[PDB]
Image (cartoon, rainbow over all chains, first blue to last red; front, side, top):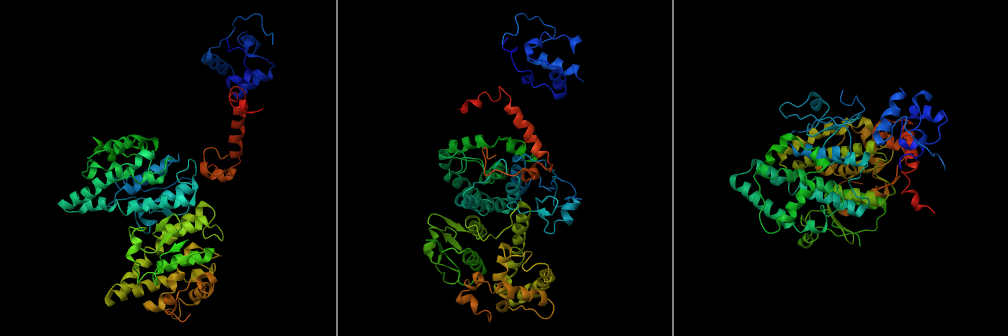
Length: 67
Length: 206
Length: 201
Length: 50
């Protein structure tokens, strides 16, 4: 998709639920589809932001990231 | 009290165009105003005591009441500026205060005379009123508004006096009414008009 | 090219003259007969009502429109507030005096001697009511002459011709006003010979 | 700014318009102008530089 390669703040997510994710040393969103829930009101906000724009949890993504 | 809040205070007229002229400029700037459709027989109490001239409408914002709609709809256009409603150039700003004076002294008294005139005057007024309103017909081709391509207060003096068209028994007729009538399609349904129009004045539209 | 169709006596035409001679506008006045200028000024004025201004492209009447033009175009010295709060005050205060007092003087000139007494004394008690307030500022609610006093200076100048006066109270804090404003060159070089002989000044 | 309007304005000169007069007005614009600063909202706007 064109929707995996964006800046992690480019989803307009909310600041504390943006701050936990970003402050926990995440790099790109194409890993976010791969990010597991065991690795992480903070849960609710990752949930609707991904289901709004066509994103999702625990997905399967190989050959990533090559810059 | 009335001024005791950080908001306005307006004692409007439910049918009197002095209010409805103020309503459009009141809401066209996006401010939260209190509506009070009150009567001359029984207005609100604060409208009687703090209003030592006792007119309608009447606006009150933390310092004193304001009336005489040109004073009212000027205080809002000079204090709450965006969007703007009056030009910048003191030449074009002069006449823009001049057309308004040529409406409150030219097309107002045809409304009062039709409110208290004889049977022929209601036609004589309607005669002088209806035909001359077609006399300014070709104006609208050059400008989408009254000689000012942006929406401005001089247009707001027309539409409320164009919303009471059949209310006092009027209908247009002649060649080129499509130009002015089609123009009414461009102004009679704006947000500043649609959200501001009182349903009491709407029912005459059917 | 800025001409003015001034009246010889009427306070309205004396109003605009104070604004012009104040700002320093280079103007030329054309007089009217008594309060009628020619029938020739109906083409640039379908109302035929004085005063009327003509500055090279523009026509204006109803001095409410005229005076705010010259204030809005010729900026200094300014004759209005600065922030929108007080301009509503001055713009409204002048609506009082042009509504209560000015038309009140109608029957004092154009009303029979019966009603002339009616307007005369009922107005006088109003005249000294704001009289103590002149102990707040020099002018009518201002520390510097502005548009709001523009309706009083040509108003006060008509006192002895109408027939009302100050006598004891209403003259102490009041008469200091006219002796402070009637000396400014703007009102000085505004005085016309027809409006001068009304009083000894 | 003077965008689509007459002369520009002062902050607390504006604050008497929204009626909440405070140093919020220096904030509302402050964080908003950051949002336009982000990418893909400045993608068309960036193109006017050089």
